[PDB]
Length: 329
Ligand SMILES: [Fe+3]
Image (cartoon, rainbow, N blue to C red):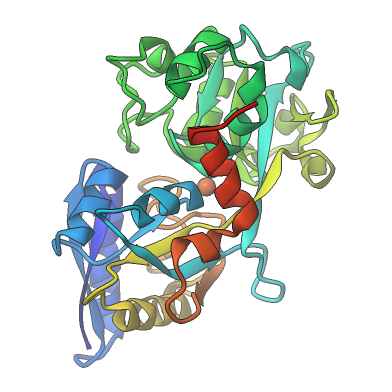
């Protein structure tokens, strides 16, 4: 019993959140957990809000989970999304590089091309691809934003500083850090490529399938494999950049309501999980893609007692992120 203040980032998420609140009210008893919606302009305002006791929960891509863990925020992962199916839940997904068929370039010929990123600091859209290309970048590689802006001939990296690094917002003026920016997130990064703004889109394995329903339309796209070859979009298991940890809901370390957060989400997935309700869907919405939780998610799993961001993410991934921030070739 009692309120979980969910942090909605911008308009579309705020609308889905208010719908969430309302449908949970209709099914959950007077003594069950309820939802309140707090709207912020970016995921960063959400991390700050939670730390400052203005909100309680927000789902973050694993790469952002690391930053949220850092002081002075010190937030921790409490609930994780899982993909695949309820039968064989996957707590990881694949980072892939989508390109158009016959565009004539491999992963080793990305210099000078235009790039579409989900957002600065995110797993598939930034950490993995930029980590792999790091030494191919021109010195000085610090700041990273400058070396990246100089490698490609223009990009859309939502949440990046357009003032200091304009080329990083060339494909999406302003580098908006929410769904208000049409080239934000997985589906936004894919639109950026489909529209012809960029040459490559750093997204996950399900993105193209979530956007193009016909196989004939998807046959016009390919994946860049690490062995400097290309494979069709269905062969991502044999052509991906890396496997990354699933998105996770984070909360305060003190007075964080993690029990209530789990109680709310567990009930939520039961009533509004995949194929559960005709009235409301937790993992989809007429208002946009990946709002509050990823559309590709099938449910939630509780994170073990007192697990910190570092242990949750793993040694490898945390090293990848570290090596990107300082990093020596
Ligand atoms: Fe992600």
